[PDB]
Amino acid sequence: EFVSEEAGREGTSVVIGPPDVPGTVPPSETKGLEFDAVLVVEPERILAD
Amino acid sequence: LWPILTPEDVLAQLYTSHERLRAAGAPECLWRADGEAWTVSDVPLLDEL
Amino acid sequence: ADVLVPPQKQEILERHEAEADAIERKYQRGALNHTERNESLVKIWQDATEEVGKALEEFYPADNPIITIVKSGATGNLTQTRTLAGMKGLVTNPKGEFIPRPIKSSFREGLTVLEYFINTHGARKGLADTALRTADSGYLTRRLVD
Amino acid sequence: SGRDYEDELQSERDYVAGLYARLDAERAQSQRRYAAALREHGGTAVERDAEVRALAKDIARLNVADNGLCFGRLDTLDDARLYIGRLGIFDRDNDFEPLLLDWRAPMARPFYVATAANPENMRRRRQFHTLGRKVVDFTDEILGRPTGAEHDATNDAALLAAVNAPRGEGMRDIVATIQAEQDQVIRLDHTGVLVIEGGPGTGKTVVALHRVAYLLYTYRKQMERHGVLVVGPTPAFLDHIGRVLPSLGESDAVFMTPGDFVPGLHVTAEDTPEAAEVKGSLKILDVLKAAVAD
Amino acid sequence: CYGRSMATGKLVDIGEAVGIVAAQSIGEPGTQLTMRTFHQIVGGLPRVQELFEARVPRNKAPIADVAGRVRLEESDKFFKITIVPDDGGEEVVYDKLSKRQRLRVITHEDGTEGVLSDGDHVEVGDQLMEGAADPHEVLRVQGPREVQIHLVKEVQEVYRAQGVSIHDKHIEVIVRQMLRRVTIIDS
C-alpha cells in the first residue's frame, strides 16, 4: 500500500526493514541518504540486532 | 627459511591456523575457516602489509 | 621608389589598435585571462597582417619589378613582399610562442630597436636548428637505403 | 517536473547550442589555417613550425573543451547574466562582450567562492548538469532567503522557504542564521584538517561539498594535479555525491568506499564486532609485524 | 609491375635499382617536412618515421572488426560502442574510448560533414575515432595487401599535406619490404 501510494506522489521514498521482510532494505543501506517518505518495519526488531 | 611473501599469504596463514595466531599474539577472535574470505576490516591490513 | 607602401596600411593598423584597446579594457576588467588575452591579440594581429597583405597585393601595378619577379614565378613569394613593404607581423620568442605585440614596421621603413631585438630570436632559432633538421632527414634516408 | 522548468531549460539549451555553433566555427577556421600553414607558408621553417604548432595547440584546446563546454550561469543583483565554461567566448562584433567566461577569469570567481551569506554581488548561481553537448538539467541556488520558487535538485530552497517559527524573545531571522553558519563553514581560511559535525537534516553534505569547491578553486595551483579522494559509506552515496558534486575545474575526483581502498579488490562483508574492534585499532600493527616476523 | 622510369618516360630497363632510387626520392625532400620539436599531434617527418617503423600510433584510433550497425552508449567523459554485425555474428564492443579524441567524421554522401552515430552502417576496418589506425590492427582485420595500401595511403597523405610530389610507386617499393616475411606456425 505504501509503495502504491508513493507512485502517485512526487519525490523519492523508501521502505526500511530487516532483510527477512520482502521489499525492504536495512537502515545501514541508507546511512547517508535522504528521502521524502520512509516506511519503517518492526522497530522493536531492528533495534535489537 | 625466509620465503617471499604476499599480503594474502600472511593474512591467510595467520587466520587459518591457531599456532601462527598465538605466535603473532592475536586472540582467538580472529580465527576463521577461510583465510582469503576478506572482510571490510581486512582491507587496511592488506594495504599495510 | 619601386618599393610601394599601400596607403590603406595606417587605417587598418588604427582599426586593429582599437580592437587591441578593447581587449585591454576587457582584460583590465577581469573578464579575460593573460594567456587568453595573448591568444586574442595574436589572432587580431594575424587578421591585420592578412589585410595589409591584400592591400599591398591590390595596390602594386602589374608591371612593378618587385611584384613582377614574384608573380612571374621566377622566385620569391607574396609573404616576403608583405614583409618588405607591408609589415613584418608577429615574431616568436625563444619558447616559440608568438609575442602579442607585432612588428608593425616594414623593412622599407626600418624597424625600431626593440622590434629588431625581438626579431633576432627566431632568426637565431632558424640558424641553429638547420643542422638538426638535416641530420634527421639524412637518418631517415639512410634507413630507407638500408 | 513542470512546463515552466522545461521552458527555462529549453532557453538555456538554445544558448548552449549557439555557444557550440561558435565553437565549431572557430575550430573550422583554425583547421583551415592549419592546412594553409602546412601547405603554403612562405616564411622560414622555424616560422612555419611556430605557426603550425600554435594552430595545433588551438585545435587541441578547442577539442578538450568540446565536452561540457558550459558549467553554469551567474545572475547578478544588477540582472547581468554571466556564463561560466571551459573557454572564454567573445563577440568581436560588439567590443568583446563575453558570451562565455573561462572559469579561471576573475569575473568568474564568484561561481566558486560565492555564498548565500557573503555574496559577491551575485543574486543566483545556476549549475548545468550536462552529457556531451546537451544539457541534461540545471539547478538553481539563491544567494539569500529563497521563496522556494526555482528548482534546485536538493530541495534546500523550498525547505528553507518552508521555515516556520515565531520571532522569539530576541527577534531572529532564523534563515539568516543558517546561511551565516554554512558560510562560516565554507569560507574558512584553515586549509588543514576540518571537522564538520551536525545533527541530521542540516544539509552537512552539500555544505561540505561547497567547502571543497571553494578550497579547490582558491588553491587550484597546489591541488589540481593531485585530485580529490571522496570516501563514502555505500556506492549509492557516492552516486549521490557524483550527482551533487559542484565544479572542480580541471581537477578530478576519485570515489571510494572503505572496502575499495585496496586497488583491484572490492569487499563488502563485515566481521563480528569483536573482530572488527581488534582489527580496527592501531594495536593490530603489533600483531601484523609479529605475523611477519614469524 | 614497376612501370616506366620517371626519368626516361619509358618502361624501366632490366637491372635498374629502383630501391635506391625510391629511397633517395623519399629522403631528398625530407627537410621540407615539419620536424620534431628541438625545443626539447603535428605531422610531417615524425609521423613518416612512425609509419615506416610500423609503430603503434600515439594518437591511436580503434577500427571496426566486423561490418554492422553501431549502438552508442556514451558516458560522462568516455565512449562505449557496440557493433551488431549484419552477418548475425557476435556483437563487438569497444569499451574505454576517450573523449579527448573526437568521434569519427564521415563525409559520406549522406550529408557533407557528420560524425558517427547510432544506426550507421560501419564497414570492416572502418575507423571509429579521429586519429590513426594501428597497422597491426589493419593486418589482423583486413589483411596484408590492405595493410600495404593503408601504409602507402598514410605516407602519401602526410607528404601531400606538406606540398611534396613523390610518386606512389616509390612508397610502394619501400612498403613491399615491410611485409616481406612470414612467421611459421607449423613445419
Image (spheres, coloured by chain):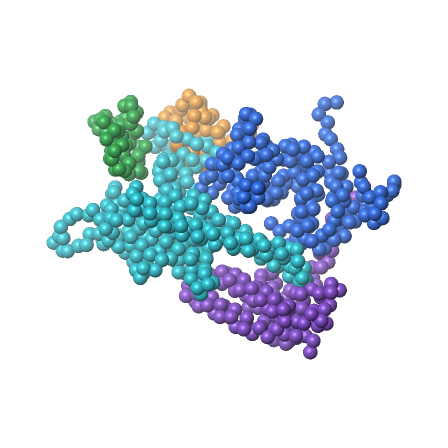
Chain colours: A green, B orange, C purple, D cyan, E blue
Q: Is C112 in front, or is D220? A: C112
Residue A16 x %, y % = 27, 30
Left or right of C49? Residue D141 is left
Left or right of C27? Residue D33 is right
Quadrant, the N terminus of chain E: top right
For image coordinates 24% across by 53% down, the residue present is: D145
Residue D110 appears in the rendering? no
Q: Is D287 in front, or is A13? A: A13
For image coordinates 15% across by 48% down, the residue present is: D165
Q: Residue furthest left?
A: D169
Residue D52 appears in the rendering? yes
Q: Can you tell which quarter of the image residue D266 is in?
A: top left
Quadrant, the C terminus of chain E: top right
Q: Residue furthest bottom?
A: C1
Relative to B6, say whether D76 is above or below.
below
Q: How many numbered callouts? A: 0
For image coordinates 74% across by 53% down, the residue present is: E29
For image coordinates 27% across by 23% down, the residue present is: A21
Residue E150 x %, y % = 67, 40
Q: Is E56 in front, or is B18? A: E56
Residue D117 x %, y % = 27, 56
Relative to E114, say whether A45 is above or below.
above
Residue B7 x %, y % = 49, 31
Q: Can you tell which quarter of the image residue A15 is in?
A: top left
